[PDB]
Amino acid sequence: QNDLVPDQWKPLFNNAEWLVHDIVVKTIYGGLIIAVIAHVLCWAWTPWIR
Amino acid sequence: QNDLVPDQWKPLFNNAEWLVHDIVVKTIYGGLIIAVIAHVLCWAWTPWIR
Amino acid sequence: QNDLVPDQWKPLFNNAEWLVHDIVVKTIYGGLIIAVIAHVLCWAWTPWIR
Amino acid sequence: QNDLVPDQWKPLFNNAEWLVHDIVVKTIYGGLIIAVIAHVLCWAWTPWIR
Amino acid sequence: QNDLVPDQWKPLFNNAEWLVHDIVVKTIYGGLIIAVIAHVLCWAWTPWIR
Amino acid sequence: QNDLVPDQWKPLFNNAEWLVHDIVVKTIYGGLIIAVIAHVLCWAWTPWIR
Amino acid sequence: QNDLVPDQWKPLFNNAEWLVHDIVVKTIYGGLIIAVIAHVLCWAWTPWIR
Amino acid sequence: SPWPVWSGYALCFVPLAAVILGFIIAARFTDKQATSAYLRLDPAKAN
Amino acid sequence: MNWIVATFMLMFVLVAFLPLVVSLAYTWVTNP
Amino acid sequence: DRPFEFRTSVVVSTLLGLVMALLIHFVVLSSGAFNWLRA
Amino acid sequence: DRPFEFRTSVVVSTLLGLVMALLIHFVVLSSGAFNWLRA
Amino acid sequence: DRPFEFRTSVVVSTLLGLVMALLIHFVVLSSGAFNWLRA
Amino acid sequence: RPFEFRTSVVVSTLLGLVMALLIHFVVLSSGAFNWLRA
Amino acid sequence: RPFEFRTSVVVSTLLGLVMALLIHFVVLSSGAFNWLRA
Amino acid sequence: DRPFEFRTSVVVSTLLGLVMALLIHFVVLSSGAFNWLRA
Amino acid sequence: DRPFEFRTSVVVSTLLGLVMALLIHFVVLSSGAFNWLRA
Amino acid sequence: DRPFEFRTSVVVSTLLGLVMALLIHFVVLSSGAFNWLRA
Amino acid sequence: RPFEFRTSVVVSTLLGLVMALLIHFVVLSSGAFNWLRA
Amino acid sequence: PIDLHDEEYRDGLEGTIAKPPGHVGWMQRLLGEGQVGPIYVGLWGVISFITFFASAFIILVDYGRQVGWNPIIYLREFWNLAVYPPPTEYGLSWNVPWDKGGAWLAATFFLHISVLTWWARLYTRAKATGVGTQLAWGFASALSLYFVIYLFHPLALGNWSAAPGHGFRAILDWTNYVSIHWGNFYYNPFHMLSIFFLLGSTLLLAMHGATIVATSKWKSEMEFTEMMAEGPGTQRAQLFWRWVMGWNANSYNIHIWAWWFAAFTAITGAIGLFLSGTLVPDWYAWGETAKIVAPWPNPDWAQYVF
Amino acid sequence: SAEVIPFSIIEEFYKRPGKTLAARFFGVDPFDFWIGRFYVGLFGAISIIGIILGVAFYLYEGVVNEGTLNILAMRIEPPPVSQGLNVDPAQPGFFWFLTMVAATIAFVGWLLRQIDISLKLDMGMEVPIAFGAVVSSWITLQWLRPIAMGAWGHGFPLGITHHLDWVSNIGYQYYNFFYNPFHAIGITLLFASTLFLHMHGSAVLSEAKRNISDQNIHVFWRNILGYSIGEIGIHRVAFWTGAASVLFSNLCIFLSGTFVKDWNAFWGFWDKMPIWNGVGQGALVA
Amino acid sequence: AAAPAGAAAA
Ligand code: BCL
Ligand code: BCL
Ligand code: BCL
Ligand code: BCL
Ligand code: BCL
Ligand SMILES: CC[C@H]1c2cc3[nH]c4c(c3C)C(=O)[C@H](C(=O)OC)c4c3nc(cc4[nH]c(cc(n2)[C@@H]1C)c(C(C)=O)c4C)[C@@H](C)[C@@H]3CCC(=O)OC/C=C(\C)CCC[C@H](C)CCC[C@H](C)CCCC(C)C
Ligand SMILES: CCCCCC/C=C/CCCCCCCCCC(=O)O[C@H](COC(=O)CCCCCCCCCCCCCCC)COP(=O)(O)OC[C@@H](O)CO
Ligand SMILES: CCCCCC/C=C\CCCCCCCCCC(=O)O[C@H](COC(=O)CCCCCCCCCCCCCCC)COP(=O)(O)OC[C@@H](O)CO
Ligand SMILES: CC(C)=CCC/C(C)=C/C=C/C(C)=C/C=C/C(C)=C/C=C/C=C(C)/C=C/C=C(C)/C=C/C1=C(C)CCCC1(C)C
Ligand SMILES: CCCCCCCCO[C@@H]1[C@@H](O)[C@H](O)[C@@H](CO)O[C@H]1O
Ligand SMILES: CCCCCCCCO[C@@H]1[C@@H](O)[C@H](O)[C@@H](CO)O[C@H]1O
Ligand SMILES: [Mn+2]
């Protein structure tokens, strides 16, 4: 079970939940990068605070 | 049972599920390619950001 | 049972399911050919993108 | 039980199911012929695509 | 109790079912002639296709 | 039971059922005669097909 | 399982709830800092008390 | 005249009296049946 | 309309829903 | 055994008679045909 | 065995008499035929 | 055992005939084509 | 026994009756034929 | 068997009947053909 | 054993295809872009 | 063991994709920005 | 032991993200501040 | 299993989300700030 | 001699389908039972199915015709689409155009047939098992009002447009219009009786459910075995209602109260609706003549104006 | 196993002293006893005081101050809306206020007495919950909505046929009341409650005096609907549906005069959503 | 003999 989990997070995660968690955090990081780029582009087009 | 699955993903997948996964991943890649082509053509037709 | 199905797809199909599958895929191929011909004829009649 | 069924379709049919299947396919063929004749007559009456 | 039924239809019919089946098919054949005559008379009265 | 019924209809009928069946068919014939006479009289009165 | 929670809070916290608590308090502090910055920026933009 | 029409008694007052009297009598008889002596499990052993 | 008294009374109307929700939650929890 | 009890007959007849008497008195009172209880 | 008990007879007759007395007083008062409680 | 019961067929046919008679009478007599029961 | 005669009889008879009634209703509402016209 | 013949027969017959009725009604209401005109 | 049975896959795909065919046909008919069934 | 099954994730993803595709097609058709199906 | 389950956390976060994305996209479309799907 | 920690965190999350949505929609529909103006 | 297994696992027309029963977990946790199927599909059950779906097909196709065969307008306008009975210019005639009343006539005939066949199904399936026929007669009492609404009140009034349209909003409109046409329905005495019985039914359902759940620790909900000998749960329920109201009931006659309170509602409603147009054309004026309307000479109308 | 018990022993077995709410708050219940068949305790005295005073005030406002002996022609009406939330002993609507307060006291006392009697017999608290639903319905009709609107003259009058005039005028002021969503939910739940009551009564009566097993009714309800609910499940469904029917209809009447003025203009958003606006032609637009 | 349902079954 708690073989691939680091020692700090053993009381919280399983073997498979750790892998699914890692997938989720990578997806969130990619989404954040894309969102920042999109917000900069839309501001360069039309600023919304005047 | 867990023979064709890579050793990293054995806790999560099976042989049948690994095969069906591969099918789904290929379908998603093809769909994304077609969607990119369609969006480029529609932008060349009439741009939707003015 | 799992005799006429290829060895790669044994964990998913029977003989009967394999036969019915083959029938379905041939039907889909024929329908797709007819659909392509119909879309070409309709575009030749009146285009829908202007 | 499976005497009249061809060797390829043994795992799917019986004698009774084979007989009923033959009746059904003959009915479908006759209906298709009648439908084609009716469509030709109705187009000769008033064409529906202009 | 299957001696009236022909050898071909033994796995599907019974003596009583064979008798009732004969009654039903005779009724259908009798009604079809009346339907034909009624349609001919109604067309002679007022045609419905113009 | 199954004594006054002809040997053909013994699998389907009974003594009491045979008697009641005879009553029913006689009633149906009488009703049909009355209906024919009523239809002739009503057509002589005022035809419904013009 | 109470071995990492301090002896002062052992009756109230578990090993997992201690870590989840720490995550929650860090999130709260970060949100408070961001909210303060946002309120300072909006006040510099247009003051709402006049 | 201060009196209702005959339909007033036919449709309104007689049905109201019937409803009230029927409720009283039905309640009397259901409570009479409920509180009689019949097969019960002994409260001492059951609890 | 004051909009402060009205929202307090709306909160009371919503709080009136609570015992039934607690009954459903109790039934769900007590029948694993 | 007799079809009906005496108690049932008494109850039915008495109730029907009382209802009918009240209904007829109130129907006759409000018609205005007789000079009875008139102001 | 008697059909009816004495208690039920007493209750029914007493209630009927009281209800009839109240109803007749109400009707005669609302008729307006007698002076009685006029202002 | 018995594939068909006489009683069920009798019930169904009788009900169908009655319903058809009622429907046909209604449709015919509510159309005004025949001079039947005219005020 | 895969197919039962009683089911086929009931279904076919009911379908025919429903179709006949529907066609009569539609033709009466169409107004194309004289039929029960005033 | 994975599939029964009676189920497929029932489903196909019902689907065909529904499609025929729907097409007939749509073509009748279209007004393109001189059919059942008042 | 297996994620999905063959029967459920067939039923779902067939139903989705029929619904899409009907939807697209009706949208194209009511759009008014093609002549088709007119006048 | 596993938090989610493959079957559930496949069903949810397919349903979400279909619903989003239909919604976007409807919004773009009713917006009027593109010619598309015009009379 | 664990105060909350991983599956419920995933479900809640995913659903909240989808709902907020749709809400913000509809508000920004309806505001009229950007061109976007004009004409 | 104790209920205090879970109850507190759930109620805090719900209250924060509701407050944020309500305040944003109140500020947007007042016109005091420019924000999303045509 | 009744074999329940044969009654539930038989083949053929006079038999069941969905033979391997399913199972739903949340129903098991909440309601206490989760098995789904098998379901009996004998005669009187195919006829109801076929006639109901014929009427439903007619209605939905006419919806589509009205919209114009446009699926998006169909989805937008689905909850305010309807098919209406022929207007007042026609009487009870059936020679009505399809888009002006013929569709309603056909669909309503098929609906009548389906409800009658469903009654027959209930009756025969009750007799086939070992139970009595009480649900069939309750359905008959419910169907009295249905046939008054759709067949007999229009027949006595003389037009088909006295009947509701087939639509989500059309029933609300029918209720409003029928109340408005014949005076005010609040002054209909049999409408008062119907409301008495309906609210009593809701009150009694809540009371019985609450008092059986409250005493369920001693298995009081096994009302079949409690009618042979009553244990602590039923004794506690009896004592509760005796110390509250001064009188109580059994685990037997409470369900008699339930049956009759639910039955009287439809009967009183049917009588009131039938009398509504044919004998008393105006209920407020009738109530004025019957001395049940309050004077109200100086209303305070500042409450009813914005 | 079972024998004939005359019901005197079952009543005398379960009588215990002091397990009520007042017995837990004060350490003793002042009126902890039985009068006839009824249990008198605290909240059993408050309720009876309220009942007597409410009946007296109602009849005085009806017979006197209106001069009518006809019980179906009284108008026990609140103050006008120009008085606000003020109470004045010298103005019309004072005996309506007194009656309303007494009735509130009576209903809350009845609820608390039900809680007491539940506590004595070691039962659950389902009956107080189900009754508190309709008590809260009365409270929102006569207290919360008048206070939020701003006057005591927004409550309904307590006349027998005249409270139906208030219902009619309020329902036609916010026309169309049928188009209220919570109204529709409440009506649906009322109809469902009546249907479920008829079904349960029929089902239990149909198996009563018969030499059959307790599994026949499950087969009956599975042959007809494909699904049989169970024995505790039906009583749970009854309880929940009964309570929810009035819980949902509190909201409709509260929101009728405070946040909404028109239930036809409420549905104006539906045709303006971007998914289907601008797709029709003349008379099929919007 | 006497039963809750009003029956008197031996
Ligand atoms: C949903 C419809 C039918 C069905 C319709 C088809 C069709 C059609 C085909 C198959 C094929 C297969 N199906 Mg199948 N199949 C079904 C149900 C099943 C089930 C099941 C238990 O339910 C199983 C196990 C299978 C299994 C299989 C495999 C045995 C077989 C090969 C898969 C493969 O390797 O190529 C699958 C292909 C990919 C994984 C990639 C292709 C997907 C593309 C990318 C999607 C977009 C296409 C578009 C043209 C894009 C291409 C160009 C891009 C720009 C690059 N099917 C259902 C019931 N199936 C294929 C076959 O027999 O020959 C190889 C095949 O052509
Ligand atoms: C409505 C469906 C009917 C049915 C109606 C028919 C009809 C009609 C036929 C069969 C045929 C068959 N049916 Mg069948 N059959 C049904 C149900 C079943 C069931 C079952 C478990 O329920 C089974 C096991 C079968 C079994 C079979 C096979 C024994 C037999 C051969 C199939 C084959 O090899 O073609 C392989 C499949 C294809 C090659 C697909 C063809 C479809 C085409 C491509 C679609 C477009 C047609 C187009 C005009 C031609 C192509 C144009 C393109 C440009 C290329 N049927 C149901 C009840 N069946 C066929 C036969 O020969 O009977 C002896 C046949 O003609
Ligand atoms: C003449 C004017 C109308 C017309 C008005 C009617 C009316 C009205 C009726 C029919 C009925 C019939 N019409 Mg026509 N019919 C018309 C035009 C047609 C046309 C056509 C192409 O134009 C056709 C094919 C028909 C065909 C039919 C048949 C469906 C049916 C014949 C009776 C039957 O089936 O016997 C079946 C056998 C019986 C009915 C036996 C009856 C049994 C007993 C005798 C019932 C007697 C009741 C008795 C009083 C009870 C007392 C017993 C006590 C114990 C004492 N009609 C014209 C338009 N038609 C009848 C029907 O639908 O019946 C089903 C019917 O009532
Ligand atoms: C004039 C108004 C200004 C403006 C002035 C401000 C000011 C002032 C503030 C914000 C703040 C916010 N603004 Mg702003 N903002 C503007 C316009 C926008 C627009 C837009 C499209 O126009 C958007 C999208 C936003 C968005 C935001 C958010 C980032 C933020 C709200 C915090 C929140 O929701 O916490 C509520 C959410 C929670 C409490 C829950 C948090 C939990 C997280 C999300 C993780 C949950 C998942 C996890 C699994 C937990 C589940 C546990 C389960 C029980 C298992 N603003 C305009 C320009 N904005 C506020 C802020 O706090 O900054 C950080 C703030 O003070
Ligand atoms: C500027 C115009 C308005 C104003 C507009 C707003 C707006 C708009 C908001 C506030 C909010 C707040 N305002 Mg203000 N506010 C004003 C003036 C004031 C005055 C004053 C004395 O004048 C006071 C005391 C406040 C006080 C407050 C607090 C109640 C609150 C910010 C603290 C907080 O709760 O964060 C505590 C910490 C948190 C909530 C942490 C949660 C943040 C986490 C990180 C979620 C972020 C979202 C993120 C995108 C999620 C990503 C998930 C991952 C990708 C998976 N305001 C003026 C009048 N105010 C915010 C609020 O109500 O939030 C509850 C808010 O949205
Ligand atoms: C929640 C779903 C339904 C429901 C259930 C419910 N009601 C309940 C219960 C439950 C579970 C009880 O346990 C309880 C009960 O039976 O206890 C004996 C009760 C009860 N619900 C009752 C009635 C009732 N419930 C109703 C409705 C409903 N109750 C629902 C639809 C209705 C209406 C109008 O729909 C009424 C009339 C009583 C039979 C009883 C409550 C007994 C009680 O509260 O006693 C206190 C007071 C008196 C006995 C006398 C009061 C006298 C007044 C003080 C004087 C008159 C003033 C009054 C304001 C005038 C009103 C005149 C009207 C014409 C306007
Ligand atoms: C339009 C409005 C019309 C209004 C009409 C109202 C009708 C009223 C009549 C009420 C029924 C009176 C019954 C009298 C006879 C019952 C005798 C009895 O006691 O019946 C017992 C059960 O009755 C019981 O639940 C008691 C009776 C059944 C329970 C109540 C049933 C009625 C339920 C509501 C129906 C209307 C009541 C309310 C109306 C608003 C069973 O006992 P047995 O083992 O058979 O006893 C054998 C011997 O000891 C001699 O009998
Ligand atoms: C909406 C209109 C207003 C509301 C009116 C409410 C009043 C009554 C409704 C119905 C009340 C009766 C209910 C069932 C009858 C009680 C049953 C009974 O009979 O119970 C009796 C209890 O009543 C006793 O003492 C006496 C109990 C007290 C009765 C008197 C209570 C009056 C309450 C005030 C009424 C309003 C007054 C307003 C003045 C203008 C005693 O019976 P026993 O001989 O000991 O029994 C024999 C044994 O089996 C048990 O001991
Ligand atoms: C519409 C119009 C305008 C008119 C309508 C016309 C019409 C239809 C009229 C109908 C009239 C009828 C039906 C009259 C009925 C009168 C009766 C029943 C009187 C009963 C008396 C009962 C009496 C005196 C009872 C006395 C009881 C006593 C003294 C009891 C005493 C006692 C008893 C029993 C118990 C304890 C000991 C105690 C001594 C106290
Ligand atoms: C079984 C149903 C009873 C049938 C009642 C028939 C009522 C006939 O009533 C019809 C009207 O409906 C019709 O509009 C006019 C046309 O001039 O003539 C009348 O006779
Ligand atoms: C428990 C609630 C008691 C009633 C609450 C209302 C307090 C009464 O207080 C009212 C104010 O609410 C009102 O604004 C003015 C005139 O309208 O007169 C005051 O007396
Ligand atoms: Mn019960």
Image: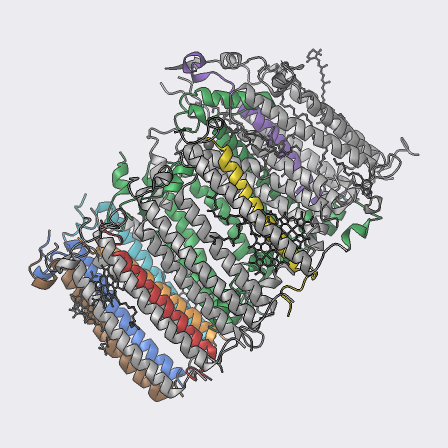
Chain colours: D brown, E blue, F cyan, H purple, M orange, O red, R yellow, S green
* Residue T282 in the image: above or below residue T247: below
User: Where residue F43 sits: x, y (%)?
Assistant: 43, 74
Query: Horizontally, is O9 left or right of S55 in the view?
Result: left
Residue placed most toward the observer, S60 or S160: S60
The spot of residue F27 in percent (x, y) is: 33, 56
Residue H3 quadrant: top right
Q: Left or right of T179: which side holds S121? A: left
Total numbered labels: 0
What residue lies at 44% left-to-right and 69% top-to-bottom? M25
Up-down: is S234 above or below S102?
above
Q: Residue H46 at what x, y percent from top left?
A: 41, 16
Horizontal arrangement in the rendering, residue E39 relative to residue T75 (left or right): left
Q: In this view, does T126 lie above or below S167?
A: above
State which quarter of the image contains the C terminus of chain S: bottom right
Q: Can residue S101 be seen in this view?
A: no
Quadrant of the image containing the N terminus of chain S: top left
| Res. O5 image quadrant | bottom left
- Answer with the quadrant where ligand 9 appears in the image: top right
Q: Relative to S89, is S230 on the left or the right?
A: left
Viewer-nearest residue: T96 or S153: T96
**Between residues F46 and T89, which one lies in front from this camera angle?**
T89
Q: Can residue O28 be seen in this view?
A: yes
Q: In which quarter of the image is residue T160?
A: top right
Task: Give the image location of residue T178, x and y in percent.
Answer: 62, 54
* Residue at position x 71%, y 46% in the image: I4
Front residue of I23 and H31: I23
